[PDB]
Image (tube, rainbow, N blue to C red):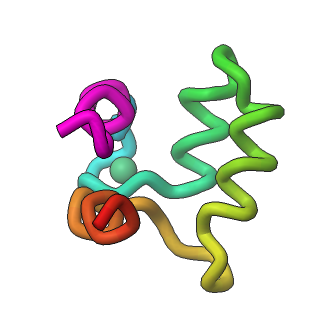
Amino acid sequence: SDDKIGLKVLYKLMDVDGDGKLTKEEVTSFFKKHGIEKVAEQVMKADANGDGYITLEEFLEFSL
Ligand SMILES: [La+3]
């Protein structure tokens, strides 16, 4: 649960783009208000793939 209960909550609430995945553009867009900065860094290191997004599946996969 705590694995990403909240992170997911907010995230799921964040994903406004229109897909369900937590992408940078979409992130910085919505996070632009939050800590897009600190988030940008964390997100940048989060992706650790190339330039994708954080999907519920990937979000739970990373927690697992
Ligand atoms: La989205």
Q: From this viewpoint, which residue is outermost toward the top?
A: 33
Question: What percent of the width, then of the height, locates residue 37?
Answer: 82, 33
The residue sitting at 29% across, 70% down in the picture is 61
For the record, the magenta segment spans 1-13
| Front one among 6 and 1 | 1
Q: From this viewpoint, which residue is outermost toward the left?
A: 1
Q: Quadrant of residue 2?
A: top left
Looking at the rendering, in which quadrant would you find the N terminus? top left
Question: What percent of the width, then of the height, locates residue 46?
Answer: 62, 62
Q: Answer yes or no: is residue 36 visible.
A: yes
| Front one among 30 and 43 | 43
Q: In the figure, 35 relative to 47: above or below? A: above
Looking at the rendering, in which quadrant would you find the C terminus? bottom left
Left or right of 50 in this view: 5:
left
Residue 58 is inside the magenta segment: no
The residue sitting at 72% across, 63% down in the picture is 45
The residue sitting at 71% across, 49% down in the picture is 42
The residue sitting at 67% across, 83% down in the picture is 50
Question: What percent of the width, then of the height, locates residue 14?
Answer: 38, 30
Q: Answer yes or no: is residue 19 visible.
A: no
Left or right of 10 in this view: 60:
left
Q: In the figure, 56 relative to 40: above or below? A: below
